[PDB]
Length: 309
Image (cartoon, rainbow, N blue to C red; front, top):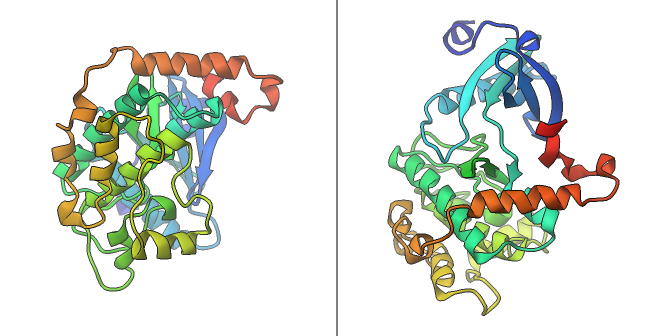
């Protein structure tokens, strides 16, 4: 318990939080919307069992993650609110969002508007320039790990694969979005946070085209490809040159040619002016459409309306 001492609140989560509903999961275990009893606020809770069979890898992960989460302070990363412990489950509480930019593309079955890709990209990029300014790497940027919360703010989530020190060398991320240099590092190599720049690139395509390139190949093949092959780009002709240059910039296959996140922050793509309501407007079409969905009880996507139930 030295770390339990150092890192957790001592209250019992089962008395603080109620009306848990699962909203996502993964290797760790599930993520839930919940109501904080003390103030009637909604939260997100990521439960991580360390009972499993082998608690060891599991617990270690938990603590590593808490230590990392304790360190963030920026409006474009998901806010961490502390963690609790009962009966071999650590609970990690966080702010709550409507949903991910993926949920956006699953609900409309349509890539977003270019303006909305810009607002989204722009916010994730602030988030990334922040981590990078602290020598952190996310390592798993994708539409899925990009959350929107009203008023209308874009935030990076899932730091499960994150690294506390650039340059790093380990083999993580999700295959289709991985950068060439993360793949090469299987073999004996290293990478910046420019790897998040690459993944942001794929994320742009994914926001523009609903799927990243290579989505239609198994992962090992996609890996051999991303690496050994030439680098993709947006496929339509119809997107501004601004957007198009952004992506080709993020997608420099050679790191020294890839601009840092700090640099992209000033790119014309992300600076061209836009309505201030974009995100909050996006969000609104997004609930309208989920409500205009048939048999709302048999909806994957009903997640988006939880706060109202």
